[PDB]
Every structure is written in C-alpha cells, then in structure tokens.
Length: 114
Length: 120
Length: 116
Length: 114
Image (tube, rainbow over all chains, first blue to last red):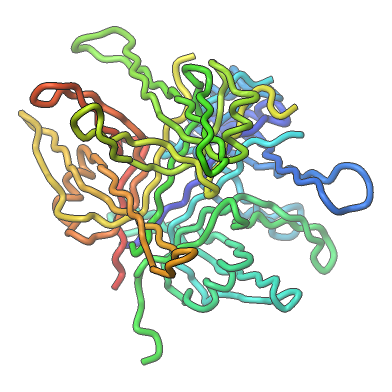
C-alpha cells in the first residue's frame, strides 16, 4: 500500500482550560493538554515515585469549539486523535512539538471529570 | 494516585534499520523509527502528494531483542506502546522528544510487510 | 498475519454489579457487563435515535477482585481486553458468546474514584 | 449518560474470500472473517499449541467495495471497527452474534508489500 495506522488514544484530564484561538480561513483550534499517569511503588528510599505524561492534544473545527465551550481543567476526556510532530522555529532555533491531533478519524468525549 | 489512559497504536514501516543497545548489556533497548503515510491528489495541481509522519518508537526487553533479530529497514510493524515525551538538554538548551514507548502494556509485531528475502 | 492483533478498547458503565466467581485453580473471575452508546438523528423512522451495545467483559486474577471490591452498577471503566468468542452448548443446542477478555495484555481502570 | 467508548482494533488475515453483497438498492456490505492467533508451548507436554480467534468483521460503503476488489483470502488487514452484538432468531430460537462493525469511526487497511 502506502499508508499505515497512526492512532493515539487518551483518557486524561485537562491541566488547563482549553487554549482556543483562530487562524486563516478562520479556523477553530483548541490546544488542550492531557495528563496520563502511571505509579508503581517499590524499592527506592523515601516517599512517592509517580510519573505523569502530559500530552499536547490539538483539536480542530467543531471539537475545537466544543472543547472551548465546555471543556474545563480537571475534566476527563477520551481522545482518539493521531500523532503529529510539527516543526516550528522558536525565537531563533528550530523546535518541534509532537501533538495529539484529533481530526475526523478520531474524536473527544468527556466523562464525569472534575 | 492518578492514572488515566495513554495509549498509542501504530501500523507502519521502519524507515531505518533498528537501533539496538544492551544495558546492563541486557537491558536491551531498540530504537526503531516507524513511518506512517497519508496521501491525497493535490487538487490545485492534480498531482500526487503525501505527508508522512515519522514515529520514534522505543522497544524494551524481549521486543527490543525480537526487533533486533528480525526487524529490518522497510519492515512493517504493529506497536502498542504509549506516549512519553522526555526532556533532555541539548548541547545548550532544553529539548523534549515525544517517543512511542512500548513497555509491557503494549508490544511489537511485524507483518510479512514489504522488502524481504534479506541476504541476497 | 501469523499471530495478528486482537484488541478491544472500551469506555463504558457497568449495567449491573459485577459477578465474581472462583474456579478450582483458586483464581477469581469477574463478569461485568459494559454498555457503550451511540445516538444519532435520521429522517426515516425515529427521533434522536440511540442504540447501545452491551459488552460482556471478563476479568481475571487481581482485576477480577478489584472489580468485585470496588465496582458497582454505574461505574465507568476502561477495558483493554481482547475478543474471545467461546462456544458452549445450552440446555440442548450449541451457543457461542463473544466476550471481552482482559488477560494481561490489557487491563481495567475506572473513572471517578478508584483504589483510593 | 448515552455514550462511552466501544472500539475494536484488529490486525489479521481473512480466513477466506470476502462475502461481498450490495444491499437491496445500492450500498454494499462486506463480511470478511479475520483470524488472530496466539500460540505457546505446553508447560508440560511441550507441544506448540495455538488458539486462534476468528473475528467476524463487517465492512460498509467504500471499504466494503475496496475489500471486494482487493482483499483476497489470506490477505492481512487492519480493522478499526467497533463491537456490535446483534440479535437474530434462528429457525426457531433467539441467537446473537457479536460482530466487528467498521462504520466511519474506524476503517480497513490491508498489508502486503511483498
């Protein structure tokens, strides 16, 4: 063929309110940041030893809007976007961010969250 | 005591042979780079186009090894790892890479895929 | 292709309290039934129509227990088991049930309150 | 309280030709049967036993067609449908089949390369 399967699945809480914004063509684009966590106590020296990944998801169109009107910090959502590392040059050098992009092929859904 | 679900699923072809290591000379860590692709005929030229994401997957333990013994450039694998963006300071500033880490909760599997008969 | 990938992912609510069982082996086996839902509109025969699949998940070992101690009707869990249609002859004919089996390769996790 | 996430992911080989049908008036419906496998040696016998699940996937629209035109037996596909147990009364009693339904939210893709 010439395609493959690039899929990301997430169940997490927004760590910050939806970071909305618009662009050319007049685009709706939410930038929520999810946080998954995985703990595993045993053999160390003190207290606690948890780890929590922070995903940089990226919504578009409706979802973007939806996110904006109803998503809040603490909420718990299920994302089915896809990996998309994007290059951008900072105030000098080139930086790239891998973000969770939910475009059609996937979709957000929230739970009872908090 | 937080958890949630951080899962990545990939079906793709390695774009470069597998980068394998062993620490402590057995904590094997493979670093294969997958490539997924998504085309479409560009409408304004009518020509063919194709953007292709390159994922940086990371295998461990057995899979790492497995990858090493049987995973070659162009091979097609199914990974079920999880997202793990990790921070590292370059030769000056701080950089972070989001890699596909396959640790237990997931696992690699290859298809007959493309480009075989290695050792002509 | 020689082994393939059989994976099921679910986010749903138990429709009834668990159903723990202990087999000779000594293991515990929870049989919670999840319910996913998908509503939608039309123009043929219906209003805002909603159909809801009922998955028959199957837990083992710890999870089975966990489920038992803290899973009740209405809880919301994330299962990562695998499809497993199993044949069994009823009080006469042969019947087969496709159940969501979570064995190692996957795992349960609940939303809103947990092992806490 | 009217959703959740019901998703099935499969990478497998059709165990035989895709049963391709074109509904009463138009849209088709493919009925390919996937086969996943899981082996292991016997902790005593040493035999290389292997259990293999057979999924009953269901394609629609394009995919259905695609399947028909290019999915040959033995083909290896990736399905991203969702679980859908459906009730039907046999030539007497009530029977229910849990099938892998690929409707929009998912999609078929075959492997090959050679």
